[PDB]
Image (cartoon, rainbow, N blue to C red):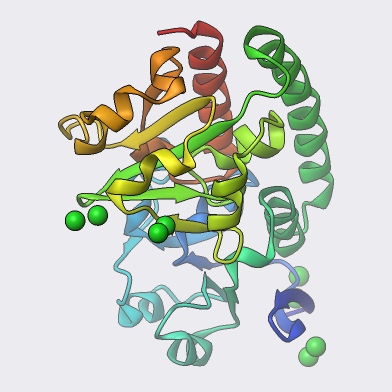
Length: 279
Ligand SMILES: [Cl-]
Ligand SMILES: [Cl-]
Ligand SMILES: [Cl-]
Ligand SMILES: [Cl-]
Ligand SMILES: [Cl-]
Ligand SMILES: [Cl-]
Ligand SMILES: [Cl-]
Ligand SMILES: [Cl-]
């Protein structure tokens, strides 16, 4: 079948990967890219079973075969003509034997560039252009509405409570970061910027939560989890955001991703909760 070169951004620059001109049987092992390809009605025949842990993505993949993270034999059984994964995938060499494989270095694409790459893969760059323009126009208005309510210089911090540890995020690591820092243009506290610049995110020792706190503090957590321990302390209660009642929780399983489906949901939810402040 006809091929085309997909130009993958990597540490080494650009890596040309020959893929089908029109991919007919895509297996998406990296859930980051699943929503975006689905949004573009890509020919997906297998998807990481991780999508089922997001309420947003689960409803979009009900009739697609689910694949275990290391189940190479499942991937092979689906007879893919294209495989999408992360460069962290231990099995990349095995996957390349099955089909053309794009193992994304996630951090090389911001969330809009990422969806543009999905458009390039499936030959729907026009659709992405329209989606992008609509997204920028909507979130530009959202930004004005939110900054008018809270203040133009409003900063925000995203914590995630996960497996009894605390994480904080840079501007493009999901958990609402793309919407908050890029689309809405809210500020990131300097200390948090510095702590997340190199890797895009960081674990936060529990004693250091206050060092990274901004005007607004958003905690991503599981709906079925009890209150995080770090929200109980005197340190927490004395944060200006917490005193101003500018602190709220969001559903981490909804907020993990940065695909167009997740983006629509989190844009709406974040705008609602920000405009409802103070709590
Ligand atoms: Cl062909
Ligand atoms: Cl090439
Ligand atoms: Cl070739
Ligand atoms: Cl073709
Ligand atoms: Cl730290
Ligand atoms: Cl700790
Ligand atoms: Cl400790
Ligand atoms: Cl320290």
